[PDB]
Image (cartoon, coloured by chain):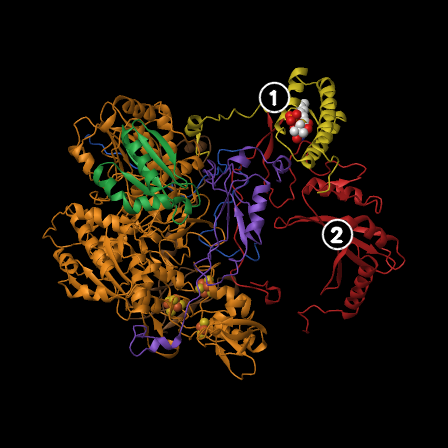
């Protein structure tokens, strides 16, 4: 098994305490486009983001707070997480169901699908 | 049955009646669209989905035109490109130059589709139109000059929301969408018209001007406002929750969330518990370190044992915290772990999971033909469940009958009455609806958990079980018995062996009460000994915090990775979006630290170890997004037959009767000012 | 500017100031937004 | 305006509280506060009257203003307000 | 298409590069895996990682391929592959006035033969590839850090390496020296989600 | 001394058929005999069935039920119920 | 898979021992040349500590790569390419001790 953890140079705190999530990003509900929901992505766990005293900017001590790796398939992401010794959490991809849509149902004769306005 | 069509020459097998747009989606082509939505009726008026069919002289509308066998769809042909460019030009001819000031900017379908399929300049040398804004409520900010008359909001209201208030007035270039009169679009699902609308015509008033989409960080989590367990996306920016958006889950909430789920995030920024508080010699709560408060609670735990120590689980508590508190109170040999929602303990009780679960599942509603609602208001207790019921009735002709107060469910039902004696009539076959239940090939009976809060809850449960058993005997593995919860923590507590109700605490008054975020006020200081020690562990100080001796600041559902089980027994895990404010910590961490200080150290130190402990108590709390099949209904019915209570003559009145009683239910909702504005608007 | 005067605006300073770094009139940065999360005020009445 | 501590308040309402250590940065120095609150300056502008039902404001100067927007003037109870400029317009009534 | 906005396409160079790619593939079938010619007239030859020295030496010495100048030598990190590191060789032929590309692959452990014997320029390029990505080049005269700090740990140009790193420097008055401490940022790098949800180029659509 | 009883059985696993039959037949009798003792029936997935018994002061013991029979489950529970 | 320098862990362990001898015999020079304010034992213990961190490694390819990086670190120390700041970075001094106890972590912050 690949154990490249000793070669990546990551400190121990960010190898064992981390919790990598492997998922396909959900579609932005504000848009009908689905081009972003095609590649598997890998992100770490959110950590403390305190307020900088001088300016109020959101400070952080998490070096891995902006890492978003994109993978073609779930298996590749799982393998990459196993390579670096990161506790991965895979979420199964959710694909919208095929839906039976009929424009003629808008004017049904004995059904509730009859619309009152167009 | 599969006919064969071609998308850009490539063969694809599609079902008869499939539209051109779905045929193109099968191969991976997403035809541009404004009016078409998967969950709304086909309109065909935006005309953006026009595509060229080979050998055909006219461009069809992919959103409406059904495919015919042998058709070759030329998605990227020159006719399609020119049609898309012309339609985009017509759409942008009268559109206002509000992009810098439009909140849809950066996440606007019209912008992206203009960039991808439209032209790069304008030939419109005339003056654009202007539309007077219409006020439709305190939530949806309306700038109607940006409307492209795609009629998504109208169809969504009329079908998913049942509110036939939105519509088009006038004709031609002067057609205007919105209510003709100055009326407020009041609905529990009104917030979704902000999402369906492609342009920034309808925008979230609380979210107005606060942030841009490209900078927000998206954290996928689970809603805890109701028991539906809707999947949501917490959009954070620089460590602050900016908005909440729905996340697609076909089996739970499809694409929608309730108004409370969408707009109650602002409650997380008010009246928060940030630092531990202990009571001084003046009887007033004063700030203190974790050391002092934990030492006090540990000493009080070491002093009393047995029934003298009790704990009341709240409404928004997580499974990990529940199991941690259970183990901690078992270390002092105390089984007084009580929830705030009363479930009938007599009989099978919280031993068989299917006894207290929506066994038919939310997605199962689309399969039923007859549904009986017993003493509940699903429009407010579980808005997404009510929406699913409405969808089933609209597309499957699902006969719905309600036993209770005649509330408006946004769909027509059969109001059998409001007396529990009708349950006996149905069970004994006297009521005509019993014959209808016999006729139904996949009947479904749903009992609201709010009805079980009555003193005769056990009798009501027994009557519903009798009806279900009569259906089972008289008429595959279709579950009939169902209980619709209203609390995000009830199911997990029942799975973790928590006693369903404060009856045990009333029976046995404790001296150490551990209020774990319990703001319901079921047990007060007057119902306890005059020297009871109360520790409140929560995020908002609403009710329990004032009547407590030590305050331990907890975390909210957006500030911790936590397991919540919805009304159908599907365990789901939230993800951390922001960190708890001030000195607040994760609940199970607080419990474990308290246990370590009190000597009785719990056998877990990390989240994974706590979830391993959850599996030891119940393995179903670690299998996320999995509705495990368990029927065990015959045993439950037989055990309920043992104790025969009496149905009271009181009518079945659900706690929520109007939209006013829906916005403010829990601590987060009550702390929210948006919910206060909504309540004021719907009352006045 | 004597020949072509600058356009007169009411918001334009009527007294130009040199670089005031190192003087008491220097610029000190600070946050301009209000406090985000409001803490809970405990009741003043005993139990 | 002035906060109770004696510290001038900005147009955003920000003012360090008396129980805030961050106010010490202003001890031997000043607090930079703009004295031209825009919200007060626009409300000072009069409401223009135009007989037409729809007008267009570019902020003045043409290309030196903002994107051109068209404002409806049908509501007699309120005045059409430019999204960028903030200028108000009213149809004579 | 045509007209000023579009970029003119030269078919002659495309044909010549395709012919030369076929030529190279025929001469070296043991290592050449794939040959491509991009629409903007750039030739790429894909070579099995054992073919670094043979193919490069052929492209340097062959009378019909005098790529005597090593234009560039870089690596591309694609963490979605078994061999994430993709080593790219850019060559220049002053005799025929053309350029060619050679692409191989390697893991985080499998070494690559050093092309110093072929091109003397490959020395520092391979040192930089090792420093930035972690790829080890066997039979290299002197492989060590070239761009990172002397006591630096980790290979930064990897896709999984954080942008801000893990450690930061400052001067401490107690120890009278510059000291490395875990990185803490006054303001966090605001990650932007910019990709549009709509497909931009239909010609690159991957199969479902 | 006993406080609660937890029985974990997988839905379709052949090694839990005995536990499934026991729950189908004798669970009602067990609950009738012991009214106030929670027999928590949860479900496993592709793992050996187990019987958990929590005693006083948070002391829990587990007994494997893999490839058992309803008679053996009854015997084990009787041993747990009494001693 | 093709090896880097050794085909067996025993062969890989041989190179580790060779590196340790070079590191062990270099520490007295490192303290002398860099004018460190530590003892020879501290440096030699530090070398042992850094070697013991990579003691769980079992893949010979990773072992070879660690030795390759180990030789590179030694060359910088021998050639005085490193400075006193670089050498003393192993001895974390300005870093405050971070407790590993749960209750200590609970008191400090939200660190998991
Ligand atoms: C002045 C202070 C200077 C400190 C710098 C010291 C260094 O350079 S440490 C670099 C050396 N690292 C290694 O040798 C890695 C060895 N890799 C391994 O797998 C070994 O631990 C072995 C092969 C398991 C043998 O080790 P064990 O005997 O099992 O244990
Ligand atoms: S709706 Fe979209 S295109 Fe129209 S102004 Fe707003 S951002 Fe621009
Ligand atoms: S308001 Fe929005 S959703 Fe409604 S018709 Fe206009 S563009 Fe469509
Ligand atoms: S998407 Fe088909 S006409 Fe609008």
Colour yellow belongs to chain: G
Residue ranking furthest to the right: E63
What shade does chain E have? red
Q: Position of residue B436 (x, y in %)?
A: 21, 66
Residue drawn at the location 72% of the way across and 43% of the way down: E129
What shade does chain D have? brown
Q: Chain for mark 2?
A: E
Colour blue belongs to chain: C
Is E96 placed left or right of B518 in the picture? right
B198 or B245, which lies in front? B245
Quadrant in which the N terminus of chain E is drawn: bottom right
Q: Quick one: SS at disc 1? A: loop
Quadrant in which the C terminus of chain E is drawn: bottom right
Residue designated by label 2: E48
Which image quadrant for residue E123? top right
* Callout 2 touching callout 1 (CB < 8 Å): no
Residue designated by label 1: E175
Colour orange belongs to chain: B
The 10 Å Cα crowd at callout 2, few under 14, some 14 to 19, many 20 or more, is some
């Amino acid at each position: 098994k690949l154990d490249i953890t000793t070669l990546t140079g990551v400190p121990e705190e960010h190898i064992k305490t981390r919790k990598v999530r492997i998922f396909v990003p959900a579609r932005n509900n504000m848009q009908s486009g689905v081009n972003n929901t095609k590649k598997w992505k890998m992100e770490f766990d959110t950590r403390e983001r305190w307020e900088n005293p001088l300016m109020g900017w959101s400070s952080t001590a998490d070096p891995l707070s902006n890492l978003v790796l994109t993978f073609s398939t779930k298996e590749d992401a799982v393998a990459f997480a196993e390579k670096n010794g990161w506790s991965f959490d895979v979420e199964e991809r959710k694909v919208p169901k095929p839906k039976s849509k009929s424009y003629g149902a808008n004017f049904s004769w004995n059904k509730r699908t009859r619309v009152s306005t167009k | 049955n599969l006919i064969e069509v071609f998308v850009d020459g490539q063969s694809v097998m599609v079902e008869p009646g499939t539209t051109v747009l779905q045929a193109c989606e099968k191969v991976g082509m997403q035809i541009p669209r404004f009016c078409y939505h998967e969950r709304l009726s086909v309109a065909g008026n935006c005309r953006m989905c026009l595509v060229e069919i080979e050998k055909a002289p006219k461009v069809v509308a992919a959103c409406a035109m059904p495919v015919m066998k042998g058709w070759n769809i030329l998605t990227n042909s020159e006719k399609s490109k020119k049609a898309r460019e012309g339609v985009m030009e017509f759409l942008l001819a009268n559109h206002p130059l509000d992009c810098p000031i439009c909140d849809q900017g950066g996440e606007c379908d019209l912008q992206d589709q203009s960039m991808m399929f439209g032209s790069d300049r304008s030939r419109f040398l005339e003056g654009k139109r202007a539309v007077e804004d219409k006020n439709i409520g305190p939530l949806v900010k309306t700038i109607m000059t940006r409307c492209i008359q795609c009629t998504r909001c109208i169809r969504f209201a009329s079908e998913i929301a049942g509110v036939d208030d939105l519509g088009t007035t006038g004709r031609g270039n002067d057609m205007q969408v919105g209510t003709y009169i100055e009326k407020m679009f009041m609905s529990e699902l009104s917030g979704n018209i902000i999402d369906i609308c492609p342009v920034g015509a309808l925008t979230s008033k609380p979210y107005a001007f606060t942030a841009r989409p490209w900078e927000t960080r998206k954290t996928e989590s689970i809603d805890v406002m109701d028991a539906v367990g809707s999947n949501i996306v917490v959009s954070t920016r620089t460590g602050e929750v900016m908005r909440i958006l729905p996340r697609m889950h076909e089996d739970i909430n499809e694409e929608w969330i309730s108004d409370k789920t969408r707009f109650a995030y602002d409650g997380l920024k008010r009246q928060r518990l940030t630092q531990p508080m202990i009571r001084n010699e003046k009887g007033l709560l004063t700030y203190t370190t974790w050391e002092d408060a934990l030492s006090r609670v540990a000493g009080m735990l070491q002093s009393f044992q047995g029934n003298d120590v009790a704990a009341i689980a709240g409404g928004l508590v997580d499974a990990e915290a529940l199991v941690a508190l259970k183990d901690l109170l078992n270390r002092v040999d105390s089984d007084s772990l009580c929830t705030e929602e009363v479930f009938p303990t007599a009989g099978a009780g919280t031993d068989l999971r299917s006894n207290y679960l929506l066994n038919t599942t939310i997605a199962g509603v689309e399969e039923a033909d007859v549904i009986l609602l017993v003493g509940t208001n699903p429009r407010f207790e579980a808005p997404l469940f009510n929406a699913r019921i409405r969808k089933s009735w609209l597309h499957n002709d699902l006969k719905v009958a309600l036993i209770g107060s005649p509330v408006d469910l946004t769909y027509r039902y059969d109001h059998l009455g409001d007396s529990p004696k009708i349950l006996q009539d149905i069970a004994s076959g006297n009521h005509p609806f019993s014959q209808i239940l016999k006729e139904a090939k996949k009947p479904m009976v749903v009992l609201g958990s709010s009805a079980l809060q009555r003193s005769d809850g056990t009798a009501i449960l027994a009557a519903v079980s009798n009806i279900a058993q009569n259906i089972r005997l008289s008429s595959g593995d279709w579950k009939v018995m169902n209980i619709l919860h209203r609390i995000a923590s009830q199911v997990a507590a029942l799975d973790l062996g928590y006693k369903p109700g404060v009856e045990a605490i009333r029976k046995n008054p404790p001296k150490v009460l551990f209020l774990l975020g319990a703001d319901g006020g079921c047990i007060t200081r007057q119902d306890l000994p005059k020297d009871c020690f109360i520790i409140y562990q929560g995020h908002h100080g609403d009710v329990g915090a004032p009547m407590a001796d030590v305050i331990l600041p907890g975390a909210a559902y957006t500030e911790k990775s936590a397991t919540y089980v919805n009304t159908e027994g599907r365990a789901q895990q939230t993800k951390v979006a922001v960190t708890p404010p001030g000195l607040a910590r994760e609940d199970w961490k607080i419990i474990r630290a308290l246990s370590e200080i009190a000597g009785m150290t719990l056998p877990y130190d990390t989240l994974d170890q706590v979830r391993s402990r959850l599996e030891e108590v119940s393995p179903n709390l670690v299998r996320y997004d999995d509705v495990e099949g368990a029927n065990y209904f015959q045993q439950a019915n037989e055990l309920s037959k043992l104790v025969n209570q009496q149905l009271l003559a009181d009518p079945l009145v659900p706690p929520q009767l109007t939209i006013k009683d829906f916005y403010m239910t829990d601590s987060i909702s009550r702390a929210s000012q948006t919910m206060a504005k909504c309540v004021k608007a719907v009352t006045e | 500017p004597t020949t072509k005067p600058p356009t007169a605006r009411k918001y334009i300073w009527t007294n130009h100031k040199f670089n005031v770094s190192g003087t008491p009139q220097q610029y000190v940065p600070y946050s301009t937004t209000r406090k985000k999360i409001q803490e809970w005020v405990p009741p003043s009445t005993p139990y | 305006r002035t906060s109770p501590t004696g510290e001038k308040v900005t147009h955003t309402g920000q003012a360090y509280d008396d129980g805030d250590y961050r106010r010490v940065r202003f001890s031997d120095r000043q607090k930079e506060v703009n004295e031209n609150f825009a919200i007060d300056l626009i409300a000072e502008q009069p409401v223009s009257e135009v007989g037409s039902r729809v007008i267009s404001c570019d902020g003045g100067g043409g290309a030196l203003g903002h994107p051109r927007v068209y404002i409806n003037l049908d509501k007699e109870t309120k005045t059409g307000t430019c999204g960028y400029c903030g200028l108000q317009f009213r149809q004579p009534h | 298409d045509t007209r000023p906005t579009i970029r003119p396409r030269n078919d002659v160079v495309h044909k010549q590069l395709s012919a030369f790619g076929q030529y190279v593939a025929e001469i070296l079938p043991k290592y050449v895996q794939q040959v491509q010619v991009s629409c903007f007239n750039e030739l790429e030859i894909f070579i099995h990682p054992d073919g670094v020295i043979p193919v490069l030496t052929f492209l340097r010495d062959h009378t019909n391929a005098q790529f005597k100048s090593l234009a560039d030598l870089t690596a591309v990190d694609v963490p979605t592959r078994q061999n994430r590191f993709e080593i790219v060789y850019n060559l220049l032929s002053l005799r025929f006035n053309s350029r060619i590309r050679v692409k191989t692959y390697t893991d985080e452990l499998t070494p690559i033969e050093s092309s110093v014997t072929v091109y003397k320029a490959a020395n520092w390029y391979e040192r930089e590839i090792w420093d930035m990505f972690g790829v080890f080049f066997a039979n290299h005269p002197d492989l060590r850090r070239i761009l990172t700090d002397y006591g630096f740990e980790g290979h930064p140009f990897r896709k999984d390496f954080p942008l801000s790193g893990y450690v930061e420097l400052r001067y401490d008055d107690e120890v009278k020296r510059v000291v490395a401490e875990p990185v803490e940022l006054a303001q966090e790098f605001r990650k932007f989600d910019l990709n549009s949800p709509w497909e931009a180029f239909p010609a690159y659509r991957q199969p479902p | 001394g006993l406080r609660e009883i937890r029985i974990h059985l997988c839905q379709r696993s052949p090694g839990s058929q005995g536990v499934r039959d026991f729950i189908e037949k004798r669970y009602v009798e067990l609950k009738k005999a012991n009214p106030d003792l929670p027999i928590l029936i949860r479900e496993c997935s592709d793992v050996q069935p187990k019987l958990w018994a929590r005693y006083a002061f948070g002391q829990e013991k587990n007994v494997s039920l893999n490839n058992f029979s309803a008679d053996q489950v009854t015997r084990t529970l009787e041993n747990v119920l009494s001693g | 898979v093709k090896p880097i320098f050794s085909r067996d862990m025993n062969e890989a362990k041989r190179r580790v021992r060779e590196l340790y001898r070079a590191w062990y015999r270099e520490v007295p020079n490192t303290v002398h040349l860099f004018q460190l304010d530590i003892s020879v034992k501290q440096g030699r213990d530090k070398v042992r500590e850094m070697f013991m961190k990579n003691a769980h490694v079992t893949d010979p390819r990773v072992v070879d790569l660690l030795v390759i990086k180990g030789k590179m670190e030694l060359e910088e120390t021998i050639n005085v390419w490193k400075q006193r700041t670089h050498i003393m970075r192993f001895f974390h001094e300005t870093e405050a001790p971070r407790p590993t106890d749960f209750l200590s972590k609970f008191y400090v912050g939200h660190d998991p």
